[PDB]
Amino acid sequence: IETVPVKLKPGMDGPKVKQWPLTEEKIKALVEICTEMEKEGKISKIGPENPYNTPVFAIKKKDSTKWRKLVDFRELNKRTQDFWPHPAGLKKKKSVTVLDVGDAYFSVPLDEDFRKYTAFTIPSINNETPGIRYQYNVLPQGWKGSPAIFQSSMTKILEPFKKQNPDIVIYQYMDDLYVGSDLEIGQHRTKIEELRQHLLRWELHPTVQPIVLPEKDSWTVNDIQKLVGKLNWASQIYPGIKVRQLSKLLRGTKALTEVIPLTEEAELELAENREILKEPVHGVYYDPSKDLIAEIQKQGQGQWTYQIYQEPFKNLKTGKYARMRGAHTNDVKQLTEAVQKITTESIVIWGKTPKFKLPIQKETWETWWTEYWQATWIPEWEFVNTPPLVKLWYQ
Amino acid sequence: MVPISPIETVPVKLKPGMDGPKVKQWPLTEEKIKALVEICTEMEKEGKISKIGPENPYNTPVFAIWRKLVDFRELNKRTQDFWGIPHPAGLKKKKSVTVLDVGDAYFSVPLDEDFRKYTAFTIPSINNETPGIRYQYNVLPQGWKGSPAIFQSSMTKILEPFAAQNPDIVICQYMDDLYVGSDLEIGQHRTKIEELRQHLLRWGLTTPDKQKEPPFLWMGYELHPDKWTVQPIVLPEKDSWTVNDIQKLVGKLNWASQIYPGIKVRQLSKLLRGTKALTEVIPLTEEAELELAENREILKEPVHGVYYDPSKDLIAEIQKQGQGQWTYQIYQEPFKNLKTGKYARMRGAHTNDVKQLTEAVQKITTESIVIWGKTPKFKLPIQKETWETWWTEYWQATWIPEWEFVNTPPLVKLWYQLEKEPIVGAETFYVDGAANRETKLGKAGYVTNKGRQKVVPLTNTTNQKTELQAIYLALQDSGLEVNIVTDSQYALGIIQAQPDKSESELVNQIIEQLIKKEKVYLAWVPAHKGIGGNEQVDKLV
Ligand SMILES: N#Cc1ccc2c(Oc3ccccc3OCCn3ccc(=O)[nH]c3=O)cccc2c1
Ligand SMILES: [Mg+2]
Ligand SMILES: [Mg+2]
C-alpha cells in the first residue's frame, strides 16, 4: 500500500533501448492487454517528455491459447542499484514445482519518481502510426526490484504454509516461485493446489557427468586415435591422464580401419585413465562474485550437450538434452528450449542465470528466438562462430 | 468567439548539471533589424510571442534571411532528450486518399510556461544606442529539439477520438502532415475530410481546402493511386570520379534498388575501402565500368511497385547474382512486385552459398516484419534435400521460415560432403607440414599405408599454410575415396566450416579437390604426442 523509495546505480541514466519489430498478431495482443491493463491503472500512457524505452513483446505459455506480455528488462535491471537468501537445499530436494506469481506483483504500487524508467512502446506496422507509450504504476513483471520489494509481502503470505510443514523448500526468482519437496507427485499435486488456493485467499526432478571412454574387444586405428584425442583433451581437466602407451600402438603407419590389438601396458594405461576419470574434478568451487558461463553444442538428432562453468576446464555442471517436444524440424526452437531449461536449472542451483555462448549466428537467433520463448526471464548470450572440436568429446 | 479547446502543454526540464543559454547577440545590418522588428511585431500581435525584461538571464542569437532564423544550438545542448518513414509497398490500397497539412504546426502548439523563459532572444537596436528588444516564445520554436515530439504527441492526442469514432477511415500521421485514406464513396470521403478539418479547427489546427491531388511526391517516392515508384534517379556523369561522388552514387543506386531489380553496388562499394577523403580520385575496373553501365541499363525502363493487399499471400523470391550478391523480389501477384531489394555478403575469410542464402532470408524477414508485419513465404533456388542435408549436418543451429523450391539456375548446392566414419578400402593419408618462423622456409607432405610418400619444400610460408598445403597434396595424389589424418586444428576448423569459396587460393584449390572426390574422411589427432604414421620428422627438417 506504500511505495518503498527506489533509485538507480550511481552514475547511470535510465535505459534507452530500441523496440525491435513485432508481428501483427503480437502487436494486437499487446494492444488488447495494455488497454485492459490501462483500465486497471496498472499502466498509464505517457508523453514525449520521457526519453526512456524498454523493449516489449508477446508470448504464449503452454496450456494457454491466451497471450502473455513479456517485457525485456535486462538493461533496466542492470541499471538498477543493487538491491539489498539462497536455499542450497532446493537443488537437493527430490522434486521442484514452478509457479507464476506475477499476478500478485500488480497490487504493490511503484515509486512515483522511478516510474519513468519502466516506460515501453507498443510498435506499429510500417511506422504508419506512432507507437503507443506506457509506464508502470505498479511493480512490473520481469523487473529485478519487483521480487525484492514484494519479498516482505511474500514472506507474510508464506508464513502459515512454511510454518505448517517445514520440510518444503520455497524459493523466489523474478516472477517465478519454486517449491521443492520429497513428497509423492499425487500428494505433491494436491499440496501445490493447496498452495494455489492459499495464493487465491491473499514440474522438475532435481550431477556433473563423468567423462567416459569406450569399452571394446577390438580397436581400430581410428578408435585409438579418437581415444587418444579425448584423453589428451581430458588431460587439461584431470592431472594424471597419460596417453603415451596408447600412442605407441599407433606407431608405424596403418589404415584407419585396421584393427590394432591392445598391449598390456596400453590396457593398463587405459584402465588407470578410467580410474582417474571416475574421481571428481580437483578443487571445483562456485564463486558468487563470478559470472556463470553456459556453453551449448548441437549433437544432431535432437541431441544437445551443455556445460556450466565459471572457469575454463572447471565445470560446475554438465548435461544432455534429447527432449523432443514439437521441435523436430526446427533447430532454433530446440536451442531456445535448451537455453530455457539450462537457465531454469541454473536458477535452482546457484540462484542466478548463466551467460550463454550459443552455437548459432547472431542474426538467425535475433530474428527467431522470441517466437519460441515461454520464460518470464531472459539471460545474456554470446555467439560462437568457430566450430568446436569438443563436440565429439562431450558425446 | 468560438472557445478553442486548450492543448495541455508538455513539461520540459533542462539537462541536470547544465544551465540556461548565455551567448552574445550578432552585429546585424539595419535592414535585417527592421525586418525582424516587423516580424516580431505581427508575431506578438498573433500571440505567438511576448516581450520580457532584463530579469531573464538567458539569450539566444538571432538572424534574418524576410525570415527570422533563431539559433537554438546552444539551447539544444541544454535541453533534455525527447523520445523510420512508412514504406509505400506496405501501404494498403484505398478508394480515396487525401493529404492535409497543418500550417504553423509548431506555433499552433503552446509551450510549457516554466520553459518559455529559456527561449528568450534579443533584437539589436540600430547603432547599439538602445537596449536590444527582448522576446520570448509562447509556442514551439522552429529549430527546437523538443518541438517535433511535443507536436506529434499533441496531434496524436487530438486525433484519437476522430479515429475511434470513424473505424471506416484510415489515417496516418507523419510530421506536420496527415494522410487520410478510405474505401467509402467519394462524396462521403470529402465530407469526412471537411469534418476532420473542422475537428482540427476546434483545437486551432488549420488545414487547406480544395487538396494536392495525386501523384504525390513524398520522401523520394512517387505515390500514384494504383501504384508507387521512386523519383527519377540522377547518376552524375564525371570523367574522373570522386570518393564523395561514390558515396552519392552508391547511396542513389541503393535507393533505386528497392524497386528496380538487379542493381549491383559491389565494385563501387569495394572501391571505397580506406579512402576517407572527398577529393580522392579512384579508378574503375572493367567489371566496375560494366556494372555501372548495366546499372544505367536497368534505369532506362521505368518500373512501378503495387500496394499491399492483406487478403493475399506475401511472397519473397530470391536469386543468386554471384560474388556474394543476392537479389530478391517481394510480391503479391506474379510479375507485380510489392518491392525489391538486394543482400551483399558480410566481409569474411571463408563462406558458402547456403549461409549467405540464410542471411538473406533473415534480412528479408526482418524487413517484411517491419513493413507488412508478417513473414513472407519464400521461393528459394535450393532443393529441399540440399537444405535438409545442410541443416541436419551443420554444427550450428540454423533455420529458414516456410519456403518452397523454385528452379531458376544457378541453384544453391552442397559441393562436397565429408564422411562421418573412416572409409574402408580407402588409402589413409597421414599429412603434416611446418615452417621456420625465422627463415620462412618449410616443408609439407604425407605418408600413407600403401607406402606412398611425398615431401615438398616451400619458401615464403607459415605453419598453417603448410598444413593446408599437406592436406592439398593428400587430396591431389589420392583416388576418388580417401582417409586423411591431420594434426592441424586450423585446417580441420576451416574444412569443418565447409566453405565453397575462400579468400585464400590454397583453400580454394583444396575445395576444388574436395569437389572432385567421391568420399573424403578427415580425421584429427594431437600433434607431438607421438602418434605413429604422423610424421613431424620429415616436415620439421
Ligand atoms: N505526400 C504524400 C503522401 C500521401 C499519402 C500517403 C499515405 O496514404 C494513405 C493514408 C492512409 C491510408 C492509406 C494510404 O495510402 C494507401 C495507398 N495509396 C496511396 C496513394 C493513393 O492515391 N492511393 C492509395 O491507395 C500513406 C503514407 C504516406 C503518404 C504520403
Ligand atoms: Mg601440422
Ligand atoms: Mg605438426
Image: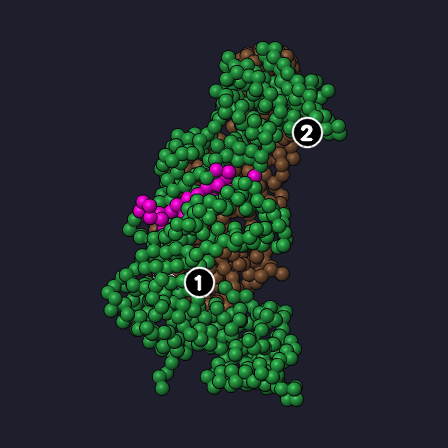
Chain colours: A brown, B green
Q: Residues within 10 Å of mark 1 (few under 14, many from 20)?
A: many
The relative height of residue A85 versus residue B432 in the rendered view (above or below) is below
- Residue, disc 2: B462
Q: Nearer the viewer, residue A1 or B468?
A: B468
Label 2 marks a residue whose chain is B
Disc 1 element: strand
Circle 2: residue type:
Thr
Q: Is residue A190 visible?
A: no
Q: Nearer the viewer, residue A90 or A348?
A: A348
Majority secondary structure in the magenta region:
strand
- Residue, disc 1: A133
Region in magenta:
B322-348
Q: Residue at x 55, y 63 (%)?
A: A6
Q: Residue at x 58, y 83 (%)?
A: B31
Circle 1: residue type:
Arg
Q: Residue at x 56, y 39 (%)?
A: B348
Q: Residues within 10 Å of mark 2 (few under 14, many from 20)?
A: some
The answer to whether the residues at label 1 and label 2 have Cβ atoms under 8 Å apart is: no
Image location (x, y in percent) of residue B105: 44, 73
Would residue B346 be counted in the magenta stretch?
yes
Label 1 marks a residue whose chain is A
Q: How many marks?
A: 2
Q: Is residue B531 left or right of residue B290?
A: right
- Residue B123 figure quarter: bottom right
